[PDB]
Image: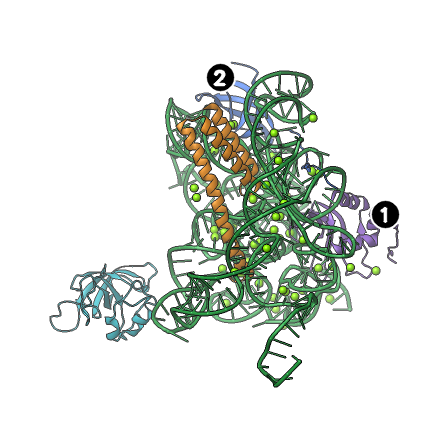
Chain colours: A cyan, B blue, C purple, D orange, E green
RNA sequence: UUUCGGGGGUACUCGAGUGGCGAACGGGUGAGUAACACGUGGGUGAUCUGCCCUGCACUUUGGGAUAAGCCUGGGAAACUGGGUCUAAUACCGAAUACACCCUGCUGGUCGCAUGGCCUGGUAGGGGAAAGCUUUUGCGGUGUGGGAUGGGCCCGCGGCCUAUCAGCUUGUUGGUGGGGUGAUGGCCUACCAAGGCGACGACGGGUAGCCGGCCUGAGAGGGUGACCGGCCACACUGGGACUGAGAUACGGCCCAGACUCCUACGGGAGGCAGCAGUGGGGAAUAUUGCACAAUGGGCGCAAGCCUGAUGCAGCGACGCCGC
């Protein structure tokens, strides 16, 4: 559940704190974004010594969503804040260390570095 | 080779704590007075004599000191912040 | 427990040692109460000098020397005078 | 914690901490009892409780957990408070 | 003894485990700090102090348990739990103390004021030990005497800047309580309103201080290489236990950033110690040998440890000789 003008947390150490969603990707009239969906987001504020400055247009993948998302066993996900991970063209993060947990859907979505490096997978 | 329980440390009398005389200028508290001391020194570089004064506040138990009097002072244990003195005696009253 | 120390001074290729009465736990070159003798073995005879009166006073009041200090002041004769078993013997060899 | 001696003294300090905390808490409870008694305003029971507190403080001070002069100062204050009240 | 798988005593010896001692010693750096932080000068009638030496009492008695070991579980790992069981200079009572530590009543000296000293006198209450070795013998509890070590308060001193004029509310002062080894807004409550301020307060920038070094006849100016006396810190910020003694560097706990291991269930770190590597730079050394001498720790000694220290290797960088 990430839409246009959606206001998100950053779970990276790239130097950015807060991002605004730009579009949700995946197809024509793409409407919602779920865990493991690559999107495009813009940086609203950042660490002064951060790698990325505010105003950049950067591709991102959402990892922490407030809305329930079911799994194959009926497992529904309610997190506490909408967060995304800054990603580059090579399907890799821009940061080196991650805040907070992650969902299993990233593993099936081939994103291996994030799921491996996260402190715990849930 | 036995005996009782006396193996002490060393003695020490009580000696000198620095004495001074100055003028009291403010008595608007009770039981405390501020005293200005007069000090004369030759300047280390110029050598010319310079007159400088400092204000030090002491302790009195009755508030018997009025404005514009001179008294003698002795050093003591700290009693509060920024006061470390007591009053000796009032020799003159104005 | 004040002990008789040997304080290091000077530079590298010649060690220095000062027979100083001071507290034990301090630094090797730490605070010095009184200087009574100096020790330096680099020279050929390695002449040794101790102030007998102050050394005797410190031994009486209770300064405990280390074994090398005890041996050196025995060479000087301070230990012999203090204990009184042989007497006071002077055998130290003077510079040529 | 990298030396065997260091970790051994860590364990020793832990067990000393437990023992001394127990002793200190016991003395604190005795002082609390005295304070409650003097707040209530008793005389005789306060007297025997003062004797017990003085005993326990003196043993603690001779055992080194608390300084003898501080124990004496506390106990003298106890006696003075009893005298005034 | 033996079947060479090993089975018994020995204390010469000893892995690991209890119990002490050291560990706050010795070495390092100058980020913060304009402060009793530094030097000098005294101080304590207001403190304490293990190991050292030395004049002077005693060291009676009873009880229980645990590590270790054995069995077992989790788990790659660190590490832990459950059950059985053992001794001590490990642990706790009780017997003396009458010379100490407290409270109430009565003298002389000193003044520097409470009051101190003359252990003043007085009535009541309270207070500790552990033994080993048979040999140059060391231990346990207390303080009339000395010394070291500390902690605290102060006269005085020492950068620039009003293009920094008001600052402060436990702030200031008194009383009563707690507090600490010691007095104290060190902390609390109640009373009053002021203290510090143009003989530069509060603000802003810089910086460890001093004996010293260079220059200058001197005054003065510059400066803090080495050594040495203190100060402050140990990746950043805090907090506390232990102990006669803590900013506790290689002690503890927590929060951060970085790094590392994993069998993904979780753990380990702090070279500004001696060497060495990466980066910055103009650039600054060798992953060297020893306790021979001396200081330091342990032990009755023998003896053990000590990048403290002695030495060696590199570099015309400097005072000096060839
Ligand atoms: Mg004695
Ligand atoms: Mg004595
Ligand atoms: Mg030292
Ligand atoms: Mg010779
Ligand atoms: Mg020896
Ligand atoms: Mg308790
Ligand atoms: Mg409590
Ligand atoms: Mg103690
Ligand atoms: Mg007291
Ligand atoms: Mg009182
Ligand atoms: Mg053994
Ligand atoms: Mg010790
Ligand atoms: Mg230590
Ligand atoms: Mg240390
Ligand atoms: Mg250095
Ligand atoms: Mg350095
Ligand atoms: Mg500094
Ligand atoms: Mg300042
Ligand atoms: Mg000690
Ligand atoms: Mg007994
Ligand atoms: Mg057992
Ligand atoms: Mg038995
Ligand atoms: Mg008993
Ligand atoms: Mg008895
Ligand atoms: Mg009696
Ligand atoms: Mg008598
Ligand atoms: Mg015993
Ligand atoms: Mg012994
Ligand atoms: Mg002074
Ligand atoms: Mg000064
Ligand atoms: Mg008070
Ligand atoms: Mg008082
Ligand atoms: Mg105070
Ligand atoms: Mg109060
Ligand atoms: Mg000078
Ligand atoms: Mg000149
Ligand atoms: Mg000049
Ligand atoms: Mg200077
Ligand atoms: Mg030095
Ligand atoms: Mg000093
Ligand atoms: Mg720190
Ligand atoms: Mg700090
Ligand atoms: Mg610390
Ligand atoms: Mg260290
Ligand atoms: Mg270290
Ligand atoms: Mg470090
Ligand atoms: Mg080093
Ligand atoms: Mg470089
Ligand atoms: Mg060079
Ligand atoms: Mg040695
Ligand atoms: Mg022998
Ligand atoms: Mg060894
Ligand atoms: Mg060795
Ligand atoms: Mg060398
Ligand atoms: Mg060159
Ligand atoms: Mg060359
Ligand atoms: Mg030459």
Q: Which quarter of the figure is the C terminus of chain C placed in?
A: bottom right
Q: Is residue E322 left or right of residue E149?
A: right
Q: Is residue C74 left or right of residue B68?
A: right
Placement of D22 over or under E68, stated as above or below: above
> Residue visible at 68% across and 37% down?
B5
Can residue C9 be seen from the camera position used here?
Answer: no
Which element is circle 2 on? Answer: loop
Subunit of label 2: B
Please identify the quarter of the rendering in which residue E122 is found.
top right
Frontmost of labels 2 and 1 is 1
Placement of E240 over or under E103, stated as above or below: below
Residue at image mark 2 = B66
Can residue A30 be seen from the camera position used here?
Answer: yes
Q: Is residue E174 left or right of residue C75?
A: left
Placement of E165 over or under C11, stated as above or below: above
Subunit of label 1: C
Residue closest to the eye, A68 or E172: A68
Residue closest to the eye, B92 or E165: B92
Residue at image mark 1 = C84
> Residue visible at 48% across and 50% down?
D18
Q: Position of residue B84 (x, y in %)?
A: 53, 30
Please identify the quarter of the rendering in which residue A19 is found.
bottom left
Alpha-carbon span between mark 2 and mark 1: 72 Å
């Amino acid at each position: 559940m990430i839409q246009q003008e959606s206001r998100l947390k950053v779970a990276d150490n790239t130097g950015a704190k807060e991002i605004l969603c730009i579009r949700v990707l995946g197809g024509s009239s793409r409407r919602y974004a779920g865990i493991g969906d690559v999107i495009v987001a813009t940086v609203k504020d950042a660490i002064p010594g951060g790698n990325v400055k505010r105003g950049d247009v950067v591709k991102a993948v959402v990892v922490r969503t407030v809305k329930e998302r079911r799994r194959a066993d009926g497992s529904y996900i309610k997190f506490d804040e909408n967060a995304a991970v800054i990603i580059k063209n090579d399907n890799d993060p821009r940061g080196t260390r991650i805040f907070g947990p992650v969902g299993r859907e990233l593993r099936e979505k081939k994103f291996m570095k994030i799921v491996s490096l996260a402190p715990e997978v849930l | 080779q036995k005996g009782p329980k006396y193996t002490p440390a060393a003695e020490k009398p009580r000696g000198r704590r620095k004495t001074a005389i100055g003028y009291v200028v403010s008595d608007k508290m009770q039981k405390t007075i501020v005293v200005e001391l007069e000090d004369r020194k030759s300047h280390p570089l110029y050598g010319k004599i310079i007159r400088t004064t400092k204000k030090v506040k002491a302790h009195d138990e009755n508030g018997e000191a009025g404005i514009g009097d001179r008294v003698s002072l002795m050093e003591t244990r700290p009693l509060s912040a920024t006061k470390r003195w007591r009053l000796v005696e009032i020799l003159e009253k104005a | 427990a004040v002990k008789i120390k040997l304080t290091r001074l000077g530079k590298i290729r010649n060690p220095q040692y000062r027979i100083i009465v001071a507290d034990a736990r301090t630094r090797r070159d730490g605070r010095a109460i009184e200087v009574i003798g100096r020790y330096h073995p680099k020279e050929e005879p390695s002449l040794i000098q101790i102030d007998s009166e102050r050394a005797q006073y410190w031994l009486g009041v209770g300064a405990q020397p280390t074994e090398p200090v005890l041996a050196l002041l025995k060479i000087t004769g301070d230990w012999q005078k203090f204990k009184g078993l042989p007497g006071a013997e002077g055998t130290l060899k003077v510079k040529e | 914690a990298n030396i065997k001696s260091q970790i051994k003294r860590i364990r020793t300090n832990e067990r000393r901490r437990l023992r001394n905390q127990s002793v200190k808490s016991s003395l604190r409870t005795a002082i609390r009892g005295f304070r409650e008694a003097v707040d209530a305003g008793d005389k005789d029971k306060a007297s025997e409780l003062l004797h017990a507190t003085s005993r326990k403080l003196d043993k603690a001070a001779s055992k080194g957990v608390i300084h003898p002069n501080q124990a004496a100062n506390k106990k003298s204050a106890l006696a003075l408070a009893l005298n005034k009240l």
